[PDB]
Amino acid sequence: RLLFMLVLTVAFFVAELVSGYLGNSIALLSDSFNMLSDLISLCVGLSAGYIARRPTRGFSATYGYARAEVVGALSNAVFLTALCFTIFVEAVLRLARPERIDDPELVLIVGVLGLLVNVVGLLILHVMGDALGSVVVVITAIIFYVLPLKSEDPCNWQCYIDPSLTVLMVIIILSSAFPLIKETAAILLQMVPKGVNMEELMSKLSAVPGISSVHEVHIWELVSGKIIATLHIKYPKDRGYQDASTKIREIFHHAGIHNVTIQFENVDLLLLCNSPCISKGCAKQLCCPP
Amino acid sequence: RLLFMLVLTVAFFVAELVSGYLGNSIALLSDSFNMLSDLISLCVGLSAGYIARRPTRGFSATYGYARAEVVGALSNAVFLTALCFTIFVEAVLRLARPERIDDPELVLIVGVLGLLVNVVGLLILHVMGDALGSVVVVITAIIFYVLPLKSEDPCNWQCYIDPSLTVLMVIIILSSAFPLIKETAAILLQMVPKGVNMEELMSKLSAVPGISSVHEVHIWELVSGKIIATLHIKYPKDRGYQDASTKIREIFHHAGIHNVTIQFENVDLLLLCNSPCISKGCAKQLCCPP
Image (cartoon, rainbow over all chains, first blue to last red):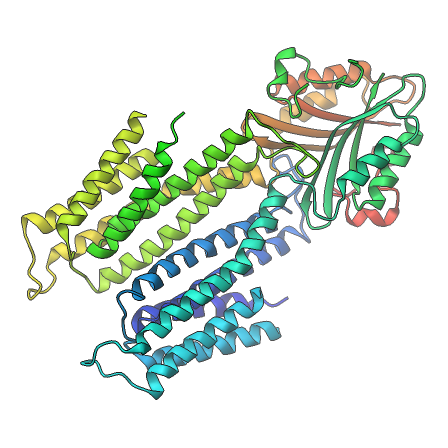
């Protein structure tokens, strides 16, 4: 992997952040915020790589720190959403009170260099967002460069180009952050992964021969590819559960789930959980209360 | 419960966002962002209240949407952290280039009314942060009121009071968001809840009579009070596991865990999981792989 992306990205985030206030460009500020999200993503990726190749799986994190990638992805998406909210609010203000670019040359140089940085990053919608933001910065600087606006003269149409394009790229960036927010939240909400079709899976689980009932089916995803399926199963007392275990495990394997914990409970009250918490008062803090 | 806090809070968020931008006050802007986080928290609380007393727990969310409170808490904390990052960056910018307050009267009125809004919200460290943010806005407005500053006159010490206090309250707000970020991330990372002392719990689990081995102990917290403990247990084949099940469940009950799924596996190599995925290639996906 490449780690020089982190130092370059943080230095360039600082550069765009300084030049955006120095040049009075929201598009440069929006691109600086987008590269801030990019460097947060790089830090999250390095954290995931460090968690891998050196697992801990101790007494504090039972599953491990694999969920760090998803938590960091959701946090980065929410961070970028708040930054885009601030950028959109500022752009709406400048759509009412327009402002000039103080140093069009500085903004042009920083935007061109940011476009080059994003190009080399892609070389080594979500991905094209940074490139389009740098293109927007370059266009805004060029308009103030090819057709200069005198300081004494009031704001012409040129002052509205930056807020409009910045609003457009706020929309573009949000159109990528929102699906990411939805996916990472769905993973973190302990929801069934999109690949797993639960209806057919429960149909097959019920169709498994020699099994009385199936309850407390809890299928959730730790990370991409790690699907955990907790499951309680009621079986006739006289018969065993070795064949049932094999069939349920192969069904889950064919459904893409390899982490299957089956609790077998001996057998209209014969459908409830035979092994809840040892007290009747535990029914409050029991998922799927009986 | 009362939901008029939502409409009042959103209206006042709009009011402070407009007034701080019209009055050029970061402290008013910081308080508007803090009340935006407050209304996000109110929306999260309403979502949690709707999830309760009306559960769904269907084929999409096995554990339900109870984790929505934690996901919304982390999202709100990250949103507020990004807003505070923007506020701190702006304040540092004004710490270099000071600015006047355009309409001190408007900022004074909005800050006083925001303090009243916080007071009435109390009537019906985050609280100290919000109250002190309103007090900071009020103080900044008063300073520009008792000693009015003419536009012709350059910025005196008065122009640096707003950025300094705003930086201070960015620190204060972050000192509350960061513990919340840590706690909600720990919950969402599938980490052992703080109350559960895993060392003693595994000691007792091993000390349980009639049990050969214990592996795949996965203790995580869905929400406050809902602790889920998946667990694989190896037991001697000749002996049963009814007494072992009772003892393990009562141990988990005394440790504060009521959702316990125990998989009992019949018995050097007699310590590995007897029921991995049906294929040897599944070991790359085995969470906690042997």
